[PDB]
Length: 74
Length: 48
Image (cartoon, rainbow over all chains, first blue to last red):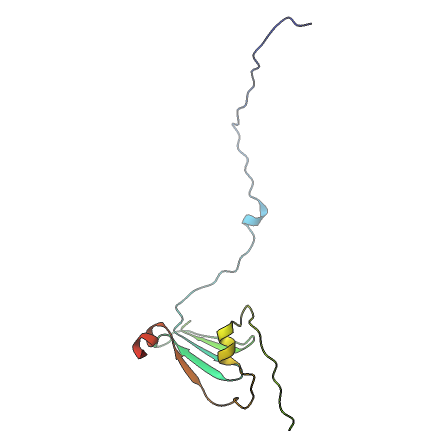
């Protein structure tokens, strides 16, 4: 039987906060140092030189993977 | 004549199109010629 009619209180208080980072926030990426390329030399069958900026080059990279390439002041 | 054959390189994640046409030639009478030069942003502005 029913004796009464009432209004339904509830305590919805969130007072605690637990947020956990999903895994992919910590995954790696590939980051690189970046300087302005002053020049480039490519050689595979035939050598080719491109010069963007002529200055005394303070750093030089050599990379052999497919074609021989030399990145000047890179 | 035992004519030498060279198989084309297609563009690759490290080997873009212009790198290929400029650093690689499929006709081997054109090998061992000499260096070609090109210009970039500033040296192009000077020469042009």
